Image (cartoon, helix red, strand yellow):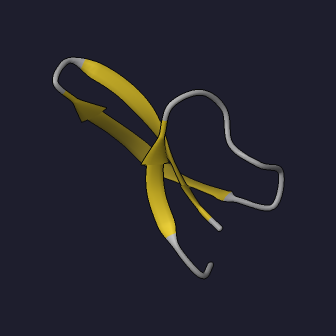
Amino acid sequence: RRTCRCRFGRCFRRESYSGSCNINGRIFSLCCR
């Protein structure tokens, strides 16, 4: 849980899915590594 951020696509297995980020009408996966 070093850094949480919205990223395009799927996340890394060790990144905890925090929530959902929607920027400019597109949803990026909010995961925290």
Q: Is residue 20 left or right of residue 25?
A: right
Q: Quadrant of residue 27?
A: top left
Q: How many marks?
A: 0
Q: Is residue 3 left or right of residue 12?
A: left
Q: Is residue 24 left or right of residue 26?
A: left
Residue 1 position, x and y percent, is: 62, 78
The structure residue drawn at horizontal position 20% and vertical position 17%, both measured from the top left corner, is: 25
Q: Quadrant of residue 21?
A: top left
- Looking at the image, is 8 positioned above or below residue 25? below
Residue 9 position, x and y percent, is: 59, 27
Residue extending farthest to the left is 24
- Looking at the image, is 10 positioned above or below residue 12? above
The structure residue drawn at horizontal position 50% and vertical position 31%, both measured from the top left corner, is: 8
The structure residue drawn at horizontal position 81% and vertical position 61%, both measured from the top left corner, is: 14
Q: Is residue 21 left or right of residue 32?
A: left
Residue 32 position, x and y percent, is: 57, 64
- Looking at the image, is 25 positioned above or below residue 15? above
The structure residue drawn at horizontal position 22% and vertical position 32%, both measured from the top left corner, is: 23
Residue extending farthest to the bottom is 2
Quadrant in which the C terminus is drawn: bottom right
Residue extending farthest to the top is 25
Residue 15 position, x and y percent, is: 70, 59
Residue extending farthest to the right is 13
